[PDB]
Image 1 (cartoon, each protein chain N blue to C red):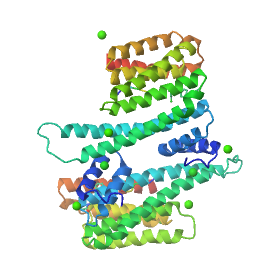
Image 2 (cartoon, chains in turn orange, blue, green, red):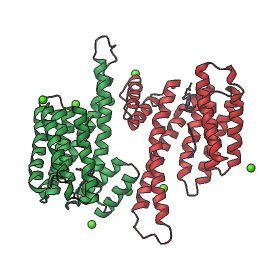
Image 3 (cartoon, rainbow over the protein chains, first blue to last red):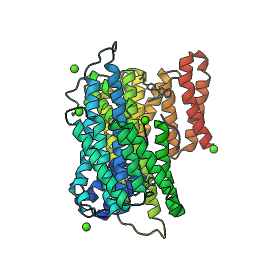
Image 4 (cartoon, rainbow over the protein chains, first blue to last red):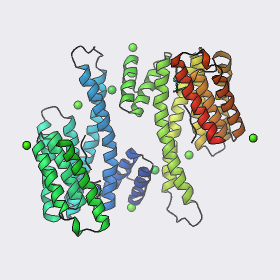
Length: 5
Length: 5
Length: 236
Length: 236
Ligand SMILES: [Ca+2]
Ligand SMILES: [Ca+2]
Ligand SMILES: [Ca+2]
Ligand SMILES: [Ca+2]
Ligand SMILES: [Ca+2]
Ligand SMILES: [Ca+2]
Ligand SMILES: [Cl-]
Ligand SMILES: [Cl-]
């Protein structure tokens, strides 16, 4: 999964 | 802490 | 509200303790209570709110994905019938997840967004609105899926418009908004080219402004820039 | 009971799904529902019950320790007064922990222990009784602390007596009982020499019986033997 903040 | 199961 | 009798300052203090103890459900309940006092949140308090709910919903999302994968395998050809239990339990987790998202969206709508006049706060809250609609979109399959996706898009877009007008290209909130909206494009909106273009443009415009920053600000901005680069590497 | 309308087999199936999803609170609730159906548990089902509650109470114990350490530091000389919040929140976590322990002890008393006639099941349940009294002892400070400690001791002792008569010295349940009772001696009963003697004797008697075992049984027994050795290394 891609990075989120 | 010591090991327990 | 359950926390109606506790002082605002005590709720904030206990949220910080809950964080230290990795008690994120408690942390979220304390921060919900703090929001419901009706006063605006500080910068630190916004972070606490975010951290609490991110951890709660993050655990739910991970569980949902595990269960969804099991359910998908059960519906493959030659898979033995095991009854309604997988679907039922996936549905249970899904409903709990949706409830958390609805709680967060409710706090934003009553009344965090409307009282937020400074760019940093308004962008922070609109980003969160986009994020929690995004989480709802991840599990949506019915006749409201398109509307949920559009609700996420609309919140992110309003946040983007404010951020570009009012914040420097290295601002951490602006960067994190772009990171997440880029992920929305890739994972939710079936727009990988838009995702890639946004991440690249964001990265490059931040790079060009780093020279203005102190050591401490530089650290913050470059951390998020590396997340943009990580996603770009994943996608290209 | 909340799970009264769900089939026993469905509760077991969902406990296994909850385990895969790392949803241990759900797992515990499913297994409580299964126990409350009134039938004896299988070997596999005993493991599920154990795993669920061990993970739930383990998280509570970790949180309690964090909060207790903060509280201890607040009561040091020259530490600034921060009000009742640390104590209150430690008390909240403590009460929740005690509630989980009381739930487990209640399942054992109604009616798992009394219906358990085979050595493996009876020892398993009495070990669990000792464990959950031990967790209550960890947080006890009042006029019942001695009685809680003695309740743990008594359960462990009955389990030990059965295990020595009825099970080989390599049996995993027997080994795990000895491991935990040894920890009780060291950490709860202020008897480190008894702790060390028990761990050593257990280890040595298991070593001498390994030659009787298949590869698979050998793996199980040697894993727990290594935990005994680890504790011995910590204590000597
Ligand atoms: Ca007040
Ligand atoms: Ca649903
Ligand atoms: Ca292209
Ligand atoms: Ca039935
Ligand atoms: Ca107490
Ligand atoms: Ca000695
Ligand atoms: Cl369910
Ligand atoms: Cl509290």
